[PDB]
Length: 105
Image (cartoon, rainbow, N blue to C red; front, top):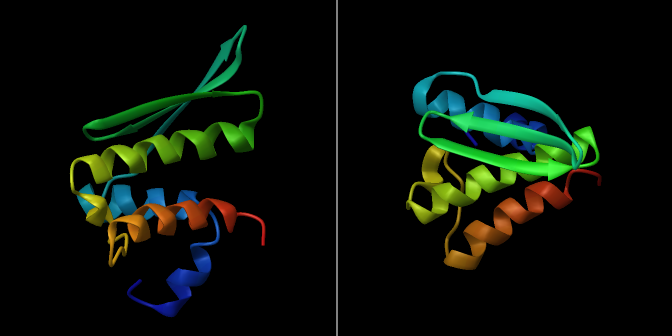
């Protein structure tokens, strides 16, 4: 956000996490890989927010996890963890949602 370059690097969803964990506590995020009959479960921890997601792929495993985290933020009116821009309600949701879709092109 500070620089246009950041917008470009925002190509991946993990960029939002790296910036969120950093701008909030200047600390890196925590990931965990589980092996269960269901497949693989990703555990994401962020200071006070912790989320988990089950998936059959590694790429989709983290993506789903990083999303659950962001959601908890909006609920606590703290979407500004890194500065998620949302002129309106749907803008905040829709904005993030696009960060996931833009994963490809």
